[PDB]
Image: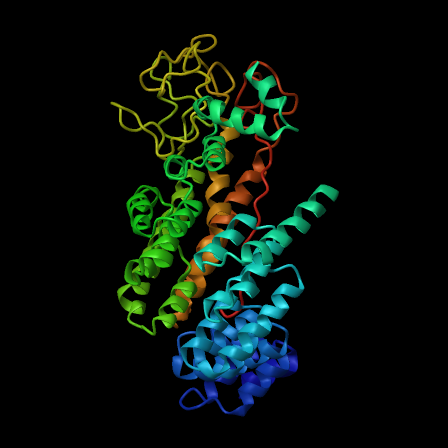
Length: 193
Length: 343
């Protein structure tokens, strides 16, 4: 406690935390260490101190990933949440950070009830900002909507694979309903370009 | 002429049809199998179009035609030709075809793991509701990826540990090689294991074989066998590096290092995520420290090489101990996209 106080007053907060960890070495780091690391952002030091202590790495990761998610640090926060099994926050950060395949896999894995909700939802956002293929495939992954999938196969100027997915579903009407008109407007605007 | 004739019907229909019917064989004989497929489609050759597509390995349209017309002939084109493309590191296309047409789950996920798309393999298994891939398939894939990455990133460490010195003869073995007739000037690819295998010399990397000094014909298929002739008969009568000896390999000494880092970094990110997902969280730090260490070493070591100044037709600056022989244009390779829970 002596060394902790000297270092706390002197501003060397890293060695202060290093000494502070020694007092509660044999139990569960009480709230003192948690509050200290949250106040000084000693998370790297507060983790390296217990880098080999899994039984307290649980709490260190919990608080650190809470900080990560609260500080716009999405992907690492989501991965740490999956490390701790924090399913809800992990899903929120995955689908917030445009993490498509992991979100779909978990949605169909443990909570199929949400598959109809989230998937098409992301299909909106991906289509919003010039991301078609990653959303085009989803419409046939589980939704099995051929037209709403090939619509982004003809819009992305992927004509050959657009016809390919229209044929692998055996749609000779889509050959003139989505492939032909999308094709037409596409090469018209390409001639303009 | 035939070309003028075919251009003469750009506004005629029956003439265009008949010129297809006549000149399609010659056009296919010329070049660019794609035009052969176009002619086959236009003239109704729906079975040899499959052969043309399987010639240059065009596959999606082959299966499309097979599904359209010949449902009995959908297994011959896909199942038989997948192996040839499989055998040469094109694992992704093989796995895609296998999963999408042949209904295979074990080897498809195995080839996804070999393709380092472990999350997509997990999604596929979730479609099949299986979780035993994690140990039978995902575990060996992750282990092999980590092992080969630790192998490859440790390969450049040796090759950069024999490059710093001014006189590039300080390889502890290259200063003794005369390289007069047994020279390895152009296909040189290694600096820490330079010139091994006295008989049938084959370097580690063979993609950097310029063949400049192989001979007058500029080709000998290797530098071990050919005449290996160049200016002023490079021998041991030289002084330092800057006199009559190797001058050309210096530029490629960094091109040999450029490729793998850029071509492997996304694989590195994906395998870090996958290998930490097993909650080790420290072999991910192993990859991180290996990568940052090798990049820092190479970038701090290439700070002693500068441009060749005025480029000259012949090697200059004979006094290599003082006349700045190892000069090389500076490269530009960046660091890794930093993660935080790996810190």
